[PDB]
Each structure stands twice: as structure tokens, then as C-alpha cells.
Amino acid sequence: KGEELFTGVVPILVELDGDVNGHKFSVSGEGEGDATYGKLTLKFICTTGKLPVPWPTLVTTFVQCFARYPDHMKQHDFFKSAMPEGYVQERTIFFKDDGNYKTRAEVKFEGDTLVNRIELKGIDFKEDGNILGHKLEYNYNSHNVYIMADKQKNGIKVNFKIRHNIEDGSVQLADHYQQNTPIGDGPVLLPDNHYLSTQSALSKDPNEKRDHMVLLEFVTAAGIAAAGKAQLDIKNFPELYRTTERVYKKSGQSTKPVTVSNIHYSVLDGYGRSGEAYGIITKDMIDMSASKPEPSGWYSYFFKNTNQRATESDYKHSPKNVSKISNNIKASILLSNGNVRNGYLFDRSGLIADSLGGRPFRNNLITGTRTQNVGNNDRKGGMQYIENKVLDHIKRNPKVHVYYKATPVYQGSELLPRAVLVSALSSDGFIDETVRVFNNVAGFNIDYQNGGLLSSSLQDTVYVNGQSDVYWYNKDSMEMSEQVALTRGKHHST
Image 1: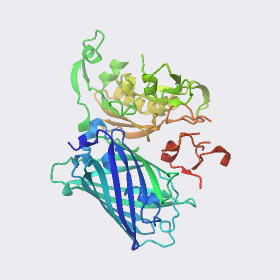
Image 2: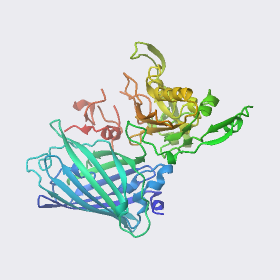
Image 3: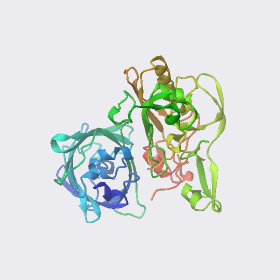
Image 4: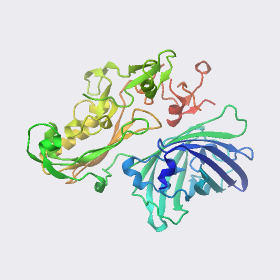
């Protein structure tokens, strides 16, 4: 019921009453959030004068109710379930070898506006340190945080570490301890453990004379965030059941009894991007598998008259005015093993492989590099490594099944994933891993935002080969968009 308040765009107001080392300041912020996309934009003003701490140290303090939860996870969304009455969010933020913030915030609706009202008290800061000395860079890195239920308080708890880059080249660490409790007495969702992935882009308003920050944030929930063990909850998987071959395959003449599960593919997200796919793989599904669509990022679109970049929807709403162009590239590459690969750089890459029982629905495809998909095609890398590991294990252990999940990892509104996390847990335990498969290819600079390669309010084009920590608005002062540049931790030149 609280989730229903977030199906459209929601106005946001932020107000912070601050005291650091006994010195008072106030900040006001306003903007809007669209949880369908996990996207919010806010502009903050220090109304009392100069902000006495660095803007980046307040980004976490300045509305996790705007996270996009995948549909099959929506039951784990505590933040929205507390609305409209809201929740209290309390943190202690320790700055290593310096002081600490303690914050208390109420996040709730006032009329049709989502308000974040915060009190902050900072103590024990060093006058010449990175904080009071303003030695932090104006940038921000992507971070994943692990949400856990706090049953004792009918809420959630989170502990996480933020890395603030410093101007000389070091990092300032900030350890965050967080507790959230409902304000209302009504029922709320107490979640299973999960992650929120956040990307934050900081900028300035050219017309704003006061001390200020513009913040663009993307927040999405996921069950997995890093490589390691399988990290799966099997209770969430579609269950094994018994049927027949022709009935499962929906084609052919074979009447052979089989044990299988129905693989779950996600609905495409608001940007049209494929999401996670999971199921239980069996020997019969493998045996039975033994006209593709194009996923997001496969084409670029441009206005015929302007030659300015268009969107796919523009192409749909008027193909007569919009050109569609393939992003793919054919090239010859030298592989690690010394072999030469002549072929297309990108594949319509299956999240759950055909060989495991996966289907060629758009929902099961990403725009993946050939390397991402098969590595060096020697069973040792890419998606192929973990697929073949599963195939081979089930071949040698025919009664064993494998819980299998492929989770694309996106940043911002980018149409190509940066990586795929593949989790596999066999029912005999011998496979128990999550691998991170990077969506890249040696030697080329991929355009993750639009697909294809990088060519030679935020800005459409800033200048960075493309891995520099600094970007410029103009080339004659010394690609990619400013939004991608900032979510990748880069900063504008001082």
C-alpha cells in the first residue's frame, strides 16, 4: 500500500539542521524522485552561508524509499511499506582519524511531498583535517550496501564504508552505521537480506551564487553484489516438478518423462534493460536443449535532420524522422592465448545459456562482448566458464541439480551492463560460487550508456584515453556524457 505512492514522480524536500564542532549551519534541498527508475535529482543550498564541511560528506545523509526493487523482490521493500507515515533513519558516521557525525532523520510525506528532515551533530573534528579543511574532491563512487532486517526494532540495519577521494591522491574513509524504524504502528515489510546499489553524480548550477550541490542518484535493489560463494536463497527459486518432454519443450514428438523447473526471466525494466534470470537446472533440461531479438544497446538512433542522438522511443514514435544504426563492430583481435579472433565484438548474449535450458527471449539477452560470453572460447573464461562447469558437473552427477542465477549489473541509466554476476549452487554442494563476468573487450572503449564504442541538468558531451580521473566541458582548455563520467567517480577540472 505504501508502494502505491511511488508509481509516479514524487516531489522531494530535504532540510538539514547541522552542528559541527559547535558551529551551526542549515541546508535546504528540493527535487523529485521516480522509483520506477530508481532515480532522484536534488539541488541543495547552504542557506546560512558557507558549508563548513565538504558537500560530498553529506551525500548519504541527504531517501532509500526511491530505490527500484525488481518485481520479484518487492516484498523486501521496507522503505516504501512504511509510507506515508514514514520512518526514522539514524546514523553514526565515523571519519577515520577524524570526527564523527550522528544524524537523525524523519522521512515521511507532508501533503504529496516526500520530506527528509535531518538533525546532524558532528564532534571531534580536526581543524586542519580533510573535513574541516575541505580537502575532499567533488566526486563520488558507486557503492553497494547490505540491508538487513532488525526484528528487535521492527526495522532494518545497514553498515557500510564510503571512500572519499582526497585532492592529494589519498582516500578518506567514512564508516556508516544505520538503523531505520517505522514511525507508524501499522504493518511493515521486514526484508530478507539484500543490497542496494547506488551511483551518485555531483555537479553545480552555473546560475547559482550560493554554496550548493546538485545531486543525481540511481538506487536499485539486488540479491547479489559481489563474487564469492553462491549466496542464493533456494526457497525463492522455481520448484522442480515432473512432466514430459514435448509438454516442457512445447514442441516435438518426444513423450519421455522429465524433471525440470520453469526458469524465471525478469520483466524488462523502465529503460528496456534485461534483468536477472534464475532457475533450477537439471540433466533433462540440458539434454532437451542439446530468430533472436536484440537487447538494449544493440542499436543507436539519430534524428535524420539534426544528426543529434535520438532515443529508441523517438524511433518508435516516428521512424520517418529517426535513423536506426547498428552499434556492432567487426574486428580482428589478439587473444590472451595468442589466437586471433576475427568477428563481431558484441553478441546477443544469453543470461541463462541455451545449453542450460535458456530461451532466446529478449528478457534473457544482454548486449555482451564476445569475450564476456565465451572468454577465449576454451572453457576457462566468460559466461562459458561457469556454464561449462555446470554442464560438466551434471554430466558426471546426473541426479544432481543446480540452482543458477544470472544478474546483470548496470550503473545509472546505461543500456549495457558493466558485468554479469553468475551464481551457481549444486544440490551436492560441490559447485558453490558467484563469478563476476566483466562486459568488456581488450583494446576498445565501450559506450555503456548507448552501446557501441565511445566516439572521438548535465552535459551531453564532456572530454576525458577515457579512464582519466578528470573531465572537461571544452577540449581547447586542456568523449562521453557528464552523467556517465560522474557515476564513474571522475570530477570536473578545478
